[PDB]
Amino acid sequence: AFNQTEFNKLLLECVVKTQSSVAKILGILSLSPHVSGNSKFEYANMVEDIREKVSSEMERFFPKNDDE
Amino acid sequence: AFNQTEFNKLLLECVVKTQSSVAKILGILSLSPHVSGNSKFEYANMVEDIREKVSSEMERFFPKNDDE
Amino acid sequence: AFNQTEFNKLLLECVVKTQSSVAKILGILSLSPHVSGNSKFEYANMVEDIREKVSSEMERFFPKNDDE
Amino acid sequence: AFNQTEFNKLLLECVVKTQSSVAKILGILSLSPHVSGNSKFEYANMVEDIREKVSSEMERFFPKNDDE
């Protein structure tokens, strides 16, 4: 017996918890001396790049414009 | 031929394994000297924040109250 | 227009790529001196714990026994 | 009331954001002195291995050949 609702709940918990955790992990590592002043890994630069990536994919599937 | 059941199994394995791994990664990094006494990255603070985030999203889709 | 097949493909790529990457990240961090001989974060211990977690969830949804 | 479209949007955002973040985390850690010249964790080697893994799973579900 496969419970799609319970599957959905587990799927959601894992991905939401992972993202919240990964956001903190990224923050911690952005502060490691071994990458200080390395532009690719400057927090603000990384956050912007991540933002673009999420936007680009979200726009393929759930565009802000609902009538292209 | 697309096997939804096998897709579901792979999806679940990846997300469950990732979350279990990320929980350990977070724990390890919380202990790095470069963030000791940095309040945003104190383990107990991070765990609480993650808890709130998971709860907030779980409540949108699978509320404890099944009759809002 | 929402393309479920393209959604499925993106979902799968992200989660598979993330898991493969997280497995490497875990390996790297397991080797950081700041957690050497800390039993919770010894690689073999972590891998076992992750294995149990994945098994426990996989068994809820896709049991090895297809007739419980 | 369960909104599959909103669920799909949250699922996608989490997994896309996580992957983008994990790619950066991997890059940062590949540069940590404690794994320099450790072949398993050399960035180019890791990227190749990840590529193979993603390809192998993508080929099971969405083969380049649509007529095997």
Image: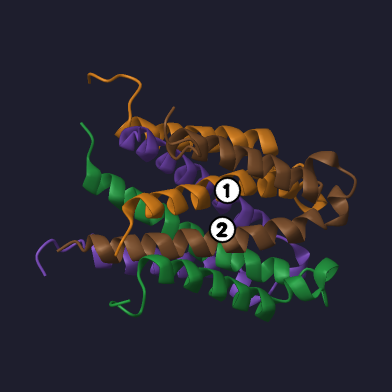
Chain colours: A orange, B brown, C green, D purple
The amino acid type of the residue labelled 1 equals: Lys
Total marks shown come to 2
Residue D37 vs residue D49: left or right? right
The numbered dot on residue B19 is: 2
- Looking at the image, is A41 positioned above or below residue D9? below
Marked residue chain, label 1: A
Marked residue chain, label 2: B
Q: Is residue D19 visible?
A: no
Per the model, the C-alpha gap separating discs 2 and 1 is 7 Å
Residue B3 vs residue C24: left or right? left
The amino acid type of the residue labelled 2 equals: Gln
Q: Which residue is mark 1?
A: A17
- Residue shown at the point (41%, 61%) measured from the top left: B12
SS class of the residue under badge 1? helix
- Looking at the image, is B2 positioned above or below residue C51? above
SS class of the residue under badge 2? helix
- Looking at the image, is B26 positioned above or below residue B49? below
Give residue B67's position: percent from left, percent from top: 42, 31
Mark 2: few, some, or many residues within 10 Å (few <14, many ≥20)? many
- Of C58 and A52, which appears nearest the observer? C58
Looking at the rendered image, the quarter that the C terminus of chain A falls into is top left
Give residue A13's position: percent from left, percent from top: 51, 49
- Residue shown at the point (72%, 50%) measured from the top left: A29
Residues tagged 2 and 1 counted as in contact (Cβ below 8 A) = yes
- Residue shown at the point (62%, 48%) measured from the top left: A22
Mark 1: few, some, or many residues within 10 Å (few <14, many ≥20)? many
